[PDB]
Image (cartoon, rainbow over all chains, first blue to last red; front, side, top):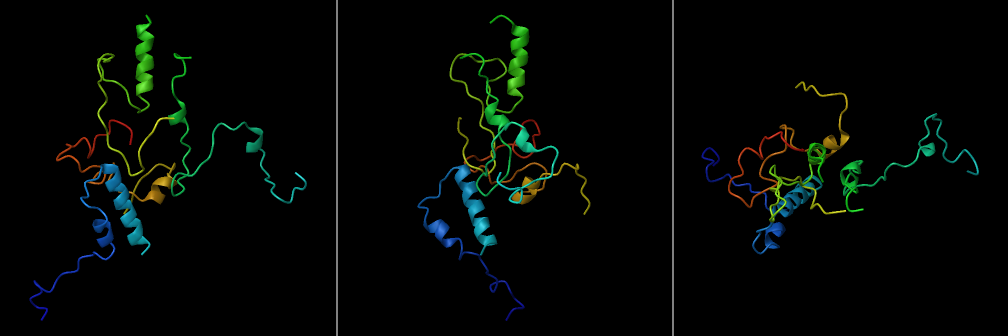
Amino acid sequence: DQLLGVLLEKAPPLSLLSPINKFQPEGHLNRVARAALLSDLKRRVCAD
Amino acid sequence: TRHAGDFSTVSEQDPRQFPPQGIFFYNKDGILTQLTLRDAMGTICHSS
Amino acid sequence: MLHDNVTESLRRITASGGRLNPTEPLPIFGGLRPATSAGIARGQASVC
Amino acid sequence: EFVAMPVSTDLQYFRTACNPRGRASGMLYMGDRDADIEAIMFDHTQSD
């Protein structure tokens, strides 16, 4: 059941990331905006 | 001051007697940095 | 201005601070601007 | 591990807790260009 764990291995963290990709229609932002979004995501993950 | 029991510091080099050479502020989360020389250097020697 | 030997030193001193400055040949004509450098996740700089 | 640093430590750097691999690098302050050469990875020619 788990000896051949090729198909039974999928743990993508998306619960805290789904809104951040749903809000953006395209996501083509600048470097400052990308860095701010990354810092906000890191802070949210730390304070979860 | 009305009394010395409110806020008294026993320090020979009291900062009160020295003139204020800069301002104190908190950047975003509260990063205490004395960032005054960089924005106060300027030129102020030609246009005036 | 005729004191080139001191104006060059003043320009070097004011360029060693790390702010924006023209190129080595001193392009006083045209619209030449310094290349944009990398920046930390702190926001956007502005004049004062 | 043993790290040798001057006694004039920076509390702001510890509070921010950025990347300790020398100068700041990585795809965090850019993304609008394909390549940016080693000048963004390690230059040590301008301000941090």
